[PDB]
Length: 193
Image (cartoon, rainbow, N blue to C red; front, side, top):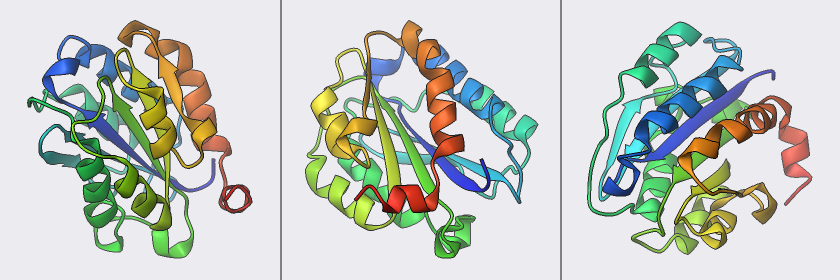
């Protein structure tokens, strides 16, 4: 993979309560495929609903076992709606920063994996533009009642968006999502607009 910064942005609103254990499994499984280390892949995770709660930053746990432990202990944030736009902007402002471990200034890809299961409670259009202008490379994964149109808007290019019918089908895309993290590189990303 070379070096990558990978941020998981996870909808923790009421709509995901039932599916949350499977969401945690999926994230763990993606991380199991990566070479996590201070000099390799760094991982961060944020939950969101009507507010955004960082769980860990890119420099919080820089070995795989520790990142996996942090994922396993996650508890549902809770909340009435997924304000996905506000959460995207929070990530750009507060997570993709040198001071919290991001290698953005050195040209390391900033991969953002967004997992949500409802239509956004806020407008994602404006935030999506800002995020991509700011150097984030998002992959929007919309589960269940999420809108693939919103995932297309959020994603680095529309074709990065993924729809899956149910939380139980997250396993079916773990391999392809891992491979994106591993295979995406700075120059290839630049070539895509």
